[PDB]
Image (cartoon, rainbow over the protein chains, first blue to last red):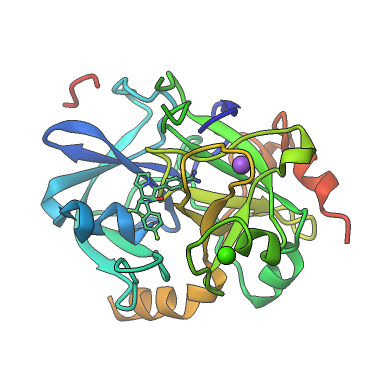
Length: 250
Length: 28
Length: 5
Ligand SMILES: NC(N)c1ccc([C@H]2[C@H]3C(=O)N(Cc4ccc(F)cc4)[C@H](C(F)F)[C@H]3[C@@H]3CCCN32)cc1
Ligand SMILES: [Ca+2]
Ligand code: NA
């Protein structure tokens, strides 16, 4: 996270670290959506142009963390993967359309002060909250700059951007399954996700019921925190029918 | 049932340091 | 990263 701040303890208890087994390293962010299911970006798991194709046995999920590098004894929980499910129409060839994946954990994780699932939006949630200028929150242990690494989880709040502005910022084809967020050059505030943060959650606190909802997944960008560029996020509600289908089936 | 309600915040009626920024942006 | 048990 570039131009963010340290998270408070228990601020993002749904935050998940995807951790490569060998070499030991941060792969991506993710989120906890139930005792048994974690949500992330498909590109965290499958991106053939860079020869990325993880199997279940290649990574671990670390839940309840604050420190990036420490083993947070008696606090974090380490979980193994039972199965990975990538959206079947994820478009890794072109523009990362439908950049979403689910992971089922081998065993259910116990909730605690530090570990608690985020809500997924329904249609009404999305309509109310996905509006230009409304701010959401992005968290992660990724790089602090485009070109180092944080001691603890970072957070930044960022406004949703008007679709034409998003479309005009990039040569990449934007779809309805994406939204963008970030400050404009003229706004004076800064902030973005970066390498290490992808797959993590973009969340909003509903002012109607005071619950946190995962509205996006950190999907892609061009550089990090560049003027006139915006981060792109997978639109979770637009893909909820697929999420439900997977959870219902498996 | 309790999704999205943080044990160290909403469950105990404490607010984090920047959630008010989010609220203030929810203007419609 | 610190080693994990
Ligand atoms: N908000 C940002 N500034 C930002 C968000 C996410 C990323 C992601 C993805 C990202 O942007 N990728 C490059 C890419 C962008 C657009 C495309 F159409 C195709 C490919 C990678 C591809 F695998 F998806 C991903 C890698 C993995 C580590 C960081 N980075 C970079 C920057
Ligand atoms: Ca364009
Ligand atoms: Na920018």
